[PDB]
Length: 390
Ligand SMILES: *[C@H]1O[C@H](CO)[C@@H](O)[C@H](O)[C@H]1NC(C)=O
Ligand SMILES: *[C@H]1O[C@H](CO)[C@@H](O)[C@H](O)[C@H]1NC(C)=O
Ligand SMILES: *[C@H]1O[C@H](CO)[C@@H](O)[C@H](O)[C@H]1NC(C)=O
Image 1 (cartoon, rainbow, N blue to C red):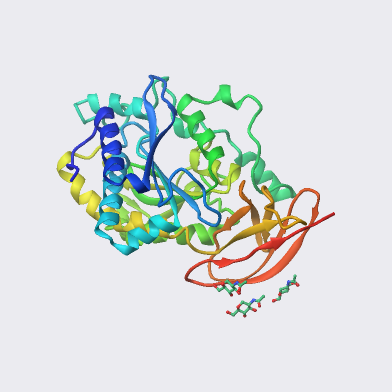
Image 2 (tube, rainbow, N blue to C red):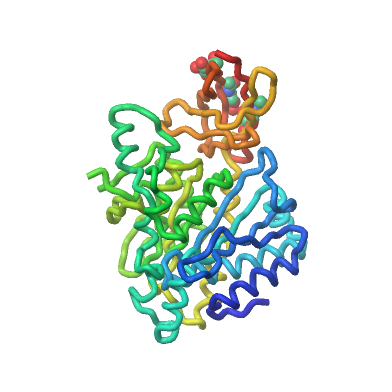
């Protein structure tokens, strides 16, 4: 079993391949790009059929260490990787089924360059700032295109409520780590995600940027539930009193806590179908090694429950006049000003709390189709659409 110590780049890489070697049939290690200094942003994928998207099977992801000195997310992801493989081998059906019905992508470190700087300071005592930024001195969580300005306007005066476009030269305005992550987001239809931070203990959800103050999304109720699921499954987050901060239910709207623009969280929601929340897991950004095991044991149940949350709401296929799959179709839910689209295979996913909704689907060159559906508290309900040409 992996030791509860801090793993630097080389050990992190060895760990991922070690897990892959132990569970060859359900894992795949791949890089989404290189850091400023040449380090690979390695991702470990779990699935009973790795390397391929299966229709109606949602894709989810965990991202940690975007801030070099926030190492807990990094270690929790390495421990989680070993845990998933072990439990699969133990034949724990909760985990086996999770892996069989979901495609899980784990990125332990989005800022490997910064981590090395943080780890060398002390060592392992970077304090509040050392290694936070990437090699070019840029804060990656202030490096993503700001799409909030557009959505706030569109919510007020009307207009597109999803997949806002990036600036023409975005590839030259972002850091290599950021660019790698954005291309990654463009490569898979991620449905649910969590970015792991350090510095506080609370489940942070959209929107991060203040409208001017609490700044909710059209999916506020859902996001609160998603945040609460992690908070209440977590060992002490739900307490609300951590690091001298008080957060009722251990959750918080980002903007309400403090305004933040150009962050990765809101980018996910406004540029893709992925609903992401930010999990602050510890007052100490770089905890001592003797605390890693307690943190792991206090987080694992929540880490599993959060991923299981992707299996709720509705999902289905959007078909054209010949009954062939229709990619990029738009699915909208009455009362919720935020749509989602079908992926390349024609399948779409829509997280929703229990209730009765009026759902509609459409696509360029086709006429809308509306249906009324009932969403239960358990598994998702299959809702397909057959569109006719305009
Ligand atoms: C589905 O039923 C609801 C009422 O429960 C209705 O408002 C909605 O228009 C129906 N959908 C269609 C396509 O008629
Ligand atoms: C979905 O099921 C609920 C009962 O659970 C029912 O009230 C609702 O009308 C159903 N939706 C449609 C379109 O029939
Ligand atoms: C999908 O499941 C829901 C209950 O979760 C049910 O109300 C709905 O009718 C089901 N879809 C179909 C096509 O039966």
